[PDB]
Image 1 (spheres, chains in turn blue, red):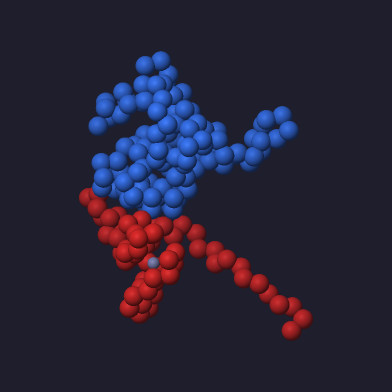
Image 2 (spheres, rainbow over the protein chains, first blue to last red):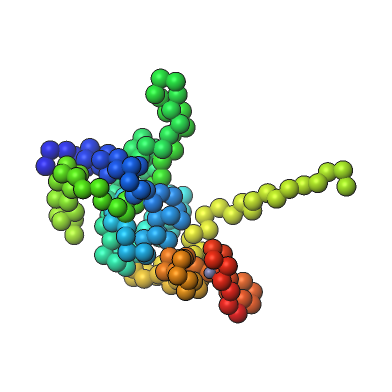
Length: 123
Length: 63
Ligand SMILES: [Zn+2]
């Protein structure tokens, strides 16, 4: 238990880029959630329609599905790793997906260390 | 015809809302028919048209 909530989660946003965990967007998260391989989730509160957040919640409740809440998808552009970077490594197109699901587990010892502790406290 | 136009994609914004009718408990009334396919079953809906029911991925069709 060394890393934080928004510190150990960049490892969750690391191997999904490597071994195909990213169910990012609006249609890739839920439509592949029902195929008994999806594991994690992060809800983002940014909405002009609260039904969007209300979509995610019952989707988290039909197969006892895990959930984290980090604030907004304008903030999550600085989290996920899907940005157009410039000549010096500075992102100019800062767009990240709100609801980021990670299906597969590349087996680690610092993301499952920190964040499974927060998972058992929540549920 | 001097100017042949092409196919603009229909700009329908935020339509996954219509796919899932979330009830007031935690249920979802799944208003669209699920495709029974082997390739694309259990995750991919079909299309409720005015008389028929049509999957788009493996091109499966019902009335
Ligand atoms: Zn089909």
